[PDB]
Length: 303
Ligand SMILES: NC(=O)c1ccc[n+]([C@@H]2O[C@H](COP(=O)([O-])OP(=O)(O)OC[C@H]3O[C@@H](n4cnc5c(N)ncnc54)[C@H](OP(=O)(O)O)[C@@H]3O)[C@@H](O)[C@H]2O)c1
Ligand SMILES: Cc1ccc(Cl)c(Nc2ccccc2C(=O)O)c1Cl
Image (cartoon, rainbow, N blue to C red; front, top):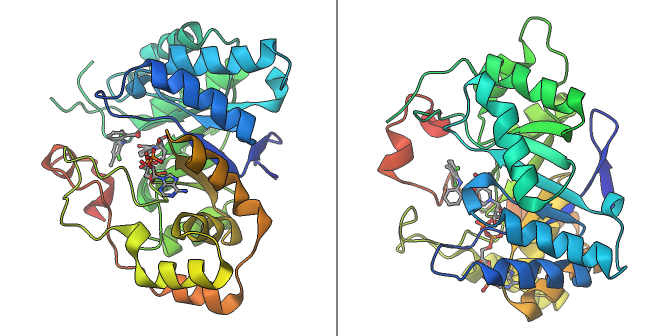
């Protein structure tokens, strides 16, 4: 199913994560994005950063061409990279992502991160970036626009902007049972802004930003015990948890069995006691924990 965004467009509540590290050949993105769509995924999450938009776009066009889905059945997201926050660069960055994917529009375009980088850190008024995003929705390049990696204060700056035309429809952020973002989720609900969870399965644990000593979410004993009770898997429990909280959840998998497994999130439900047990795992733990973000003036977790 779908959630109605605050601009009247609809977003599928389970999305397919397409990021893979650079050691995975670029051709894999094409193959697994096809498999995801075959499995039942209708929301596909990509970004300029991922260096896969040509493959992801080809998978979508491929599944349109062979007749499995129509373009309006697919919800495709791309994201403005942090070297393109200066307002005059926004629309050209978007049109480029479009030309790569060979699509006429994205369903959603996000500001990937509030941490501006030189076109080295940069200082940009993200309110001007936002105006440029608004112009992209007006031109029909993006059906909806939103943000990613914004904390409550950063999100407030946009919402409070003089002559704001469109609220962000969502804030895509790190979110899972060890970092459940409860307070930010309540703030977003109060504003009819959807929270979209990434690393909802505990991240890819890439050594470039994640400490390998960090706990492994999918071996959590409470998650294992609920998977046993429901006869599902720890990943399924972690995804269902977000859906029942009114959180749109992404799931990356480049594995054919796990891709098909993940759409089973719709086939069962958790009780209030289950949800409380998961809620009790929260431990303020963000897996991405790197000097490369932490020292930025607009680091979202400076809290
Ligand atoms: N906005 C941002 O700054 C940001 C940041 C991070 C991620 N994202 C978006 O969110 C997407 C997902 O987040 P993520 O990449 O951190 O990964 P994720 O969804 O947390 O998944 C982490 C690992 O879970 C494994 N997995 C998937 N399904 C599973 C299952 N059923 N059972 C066991 N393991 C399973 C996958 O390994 P296999 O591939 O081997 O199955 C995957 O590498 C990204 O791909 C990207 O689209 C955005
Ligand atoms: C904290 C933070 C800040 C900025 C970005 Cl862009 C990201 N996103 C990524 C970082 C490294 C590799 C992939 C991503 C992603 O968007 O998937 C995160 Cl996790």
